[PDB]
Amino acid sequence: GKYNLILSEYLSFIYNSVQIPIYYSSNSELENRCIEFHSKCLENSKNGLSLRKLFVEYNDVIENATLLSILSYSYDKYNAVERKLVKYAKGKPLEADLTVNELDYENNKMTSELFPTAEEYTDSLMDPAILTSLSSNLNAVMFWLEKHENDVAEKLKVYKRRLDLFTIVASTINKYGVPRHNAKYRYEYDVMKDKPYYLVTWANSSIEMLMSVFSHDDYLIAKELIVLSYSNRSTLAKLVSSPMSILVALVDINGTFITNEELELEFSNKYVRAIVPDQTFDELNQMLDNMRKAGLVDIPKMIQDWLVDRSIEKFPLMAKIYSWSFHVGFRKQKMLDAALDQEMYREYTMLIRDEVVKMLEEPVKHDDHLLRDSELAGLLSMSSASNGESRQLKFGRKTIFSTKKNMHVMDDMANERYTPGIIPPVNVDKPIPLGRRDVPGRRTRIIFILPYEYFIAQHAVVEKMLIYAKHTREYAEFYSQSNQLLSYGDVTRFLSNNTMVLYTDVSQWDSSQHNTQPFRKGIIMGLDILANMTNDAKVLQTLNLYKQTQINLMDSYVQIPDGNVIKKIQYGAVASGEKQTKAANSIANLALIKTVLSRISNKHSFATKIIRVDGDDNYAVLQFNTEVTKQMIQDVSNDVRETYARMNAKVKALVSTVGIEIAKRYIAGGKIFFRAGINLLNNEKRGQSTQWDQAAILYSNYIVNRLRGFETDREFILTKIMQMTSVAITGSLRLFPSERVLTTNSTFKVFDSEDFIIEYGTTVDEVYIQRAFMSLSSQKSGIADEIAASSTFKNYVTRLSEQLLFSKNNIVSRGIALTEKAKLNSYAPISLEKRRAQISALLTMLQKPVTFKSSKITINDILRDIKPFFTVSDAHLPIQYQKFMPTLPDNVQYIIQCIGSRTYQIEDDGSKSAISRLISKYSVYKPSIEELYKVISLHENEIQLYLISLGIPKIDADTYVGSKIYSRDKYRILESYVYNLLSINYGCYQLFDFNSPDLEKLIRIPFKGKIPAVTFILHLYAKLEVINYAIKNGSWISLFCNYPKSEMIKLWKKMWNITSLRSPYTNANFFQ
């Protein structure tokens, strides 16, 4: 409820020249009052008359109606930012030390000194790539400063620390003025030329950090980072983060959580003595010395202080610094510099070849259907296919330019130019265009943008590969529905005073030319063995074509931009951009550690408890037949590094007995930690999302950081959302959506009125508003239709269908057409028409609704029914689980202490149902949870046709439609679909154990009717209600269900007619 009020203070703060609160009500008479009040308000304003009496005269509308939005008319130039900033510019501007960076352009020189002409200029190295302005961020920060001006006690100190810091930004920015942005939120050469190139991006990173400062430690860290970042744009994050890799090895283990035979977390009071060889301390000191040499003082001191005792109790600071380092910004170099960095592998290539065969040995011999119809699968998959180059297309009677692979396939199929049998060359004749990957602290990487022939030639095989990984534990990232908690648990498991954990960073090795030969050689060698396992023409061809993509890649060439010219150098390293990138890289990293561990054994005798490959890291737990000593650790560590060295692998390999550190997570003191370094006011690249989507993404990012240990003041986040979600009617009229519009569960939801708690319309006004937004959920797109009617498109839909279906499929066919129609929204013209349509509708929608014949049922409606049948009563749950994830906020951590947490993902796609498995056994088609949901709920006779229409044998189709499993699936599909609509796998909930015995007690549900569907939703609704209460109140409640038996049948019917909601909030979770 505080959002609507904060919004007014902000608008009053920004404009000082009128505000017109717009209300609405499900009630008819009240709504007329709302209409009258709005009119009188506009009339008084357009006469310079007070609205004070009017607010009293319409107290009823203020008190009972729902605020829809706040109208704002201001006749100013918005140049107020220039004026407001001077009050804080009373400081000494920062002076960029143009000596800290290797590459000259990474130094905060003057924009002109890097681009003496407007024709050579490019924001490609500092572009915030976000749909919000630096001008806005400044306004937001000053607004908060004013509000917390008279604060007292500790709140004042927070204000004090922030006021200081903002002065640095204000002083430095004032020296050159505030960079004015254009409509596309892009900063041009005219504004930028007379100012430091990295000025704008730096301001965003600094503003973002300072509005996240609370404690004195935050201030110290933010101050050092904000100041050094101004000149260091390439090693600050790496320098600050390097120590953590060693620190984890230091903290002793006093009680930790492990994984048991049921793959679930379980507390163990075990104690493990961290044993660190003297040499490790030197390595740590060097990292510290380097930090000091780079101008860092406070941060190095803090680590140094921590090093006296190395207590897990005072470790939060080390973690806080580690997360903070990323908020400096991304390292955006020049394509060329990024690209430029680029007998013993006998064992290594052998393992890769063998691993390749195992993953496909069974599918190939049996003559798996997918492998046979692989090419068809690739076409269906094209949607989830990585982007390609911007080609010249022609649909129907028009010409366009698309970068989507599916569109290239349509045009190519039409003009008889579609030839998947022929896998284009990627050498000097056909140079690979290049995509990039920008991350904080690490060097920029390139991405191959190969033609679709490559994806199709690879999709089926990789999917089969991943399946093997799914049931293989070595592949931490893929194994089961497992989350990182299980991986965390596996390491702690065996840790004892006679075992040492060996972690290794291998990110550099993936792009090592030394690596590329053994790599492709191993995959192909394996492919040949696979071919010698079958005779199937379909299988051998798909198996063979994959072999071809590897050979073309063996010698690839790249189009590296160098100014306004596109050079072409011979690339000889394994870059990413393939379909097998993630899976193949995993196979290689695993092969690598297997190879290294095998070599070291010749000297030391250990036991391989576990071996793991997870992303850009790999690790293992070895057990020795004697207590581990510093000397033993030193010997194993040296031999490991030496072995990696012999293979010419630039990798960072450490050894410990208590912790580990890898890109996705780090374990220190038995506890689990996840870096909270997601940048907020600066993005990696520019996409095609809207400001609203971006606002929801920002909130989403804010939530993940907060859960991980970095908290940006919510008031600031709220203000940004206020700026980003606003809309302009005229040049002086800007409309700001209210809290209800923004937080309600609709197609326009941006955030939760209360963090970690998702609410659902529990009032008539909310339901009234919810239905209205849905009406204009999907808008028209003339262009999108032109192509839908285009022959080249129709043939495409029909061609795919005529290869999948045997009999008469329309349920599947209707889906394929609509799927494609949507698969075109990326193409700017189509999406752009949609946003404009959505906005105009939204502008009027905010004004007047009423005419909407509701008939669609959503999750909101089902819950709306159940609520009235639950009797609440205070209950009590004692804290019994020790905190294993320290950074978690208190309210969220409290739930875990009482009910615990999980280590798995809840099936929410329906893949675990028999029907889905059966369709997979015979068809390459992949029905969604939504389609399966509609299909399972059809008449037994229809299900038989649908299964057969997809190639399913009649004996099998008939056997299932009756079997007990078919009915069982019915519950599972609905259960899977519902979990999906409840975001049970995202946000905060994904952490909680919804089957906690402790939570289960608080739910008192008498089974008046043994109807699996109704019993399920009532229990889940009860669990969510109880948990949300704990999250917001710190205490518990017990829920008793007295749902009518007669009513249950009505409800059960409603359950099978639920419409899924699409929104920025929804997209934001998926975005993660």
Image (tube, rainbow, N blue to C red):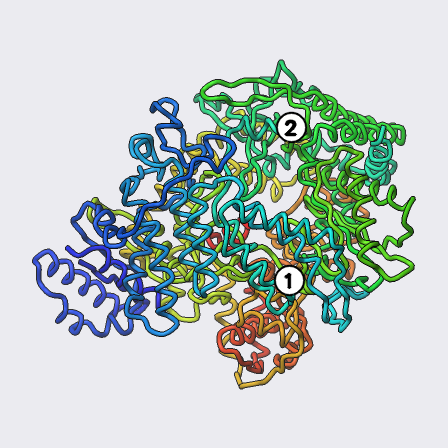
Residue 1053 figure quarter? bottom right
SS class, disc 1:
helix
Q: Is residue 982 visible?
A: no
Residue identified by numbered label 1 = 975
Q: Is residue 137 rendered to the left or right of residue 647?
A: left
x then y, percent, for residue 278 = 74, 54
Query: Which residue does the image show at 55% across and 33% down from the upper left?
Result: 436
The type of residue carrying mark 2 is Gln
Residue 124 figure quarter? top left
x then y, percent, for residue 682 = 44, 45
x then y, percent, for residue 174 = 27, 45
Q: Is residue 836 rendered to the left or right of residue 535?
A: left
Frontmost residue, 729 versus 8? 8
Q: Nearer the viewer, mark 2 or mark 1?
A: 2
Frontmost residue, 719 versus 761? 719
Q: Is residue 48 rendered to the left or right of residue 1002?
A: left
The type of residue carrying mark 1 is Glu
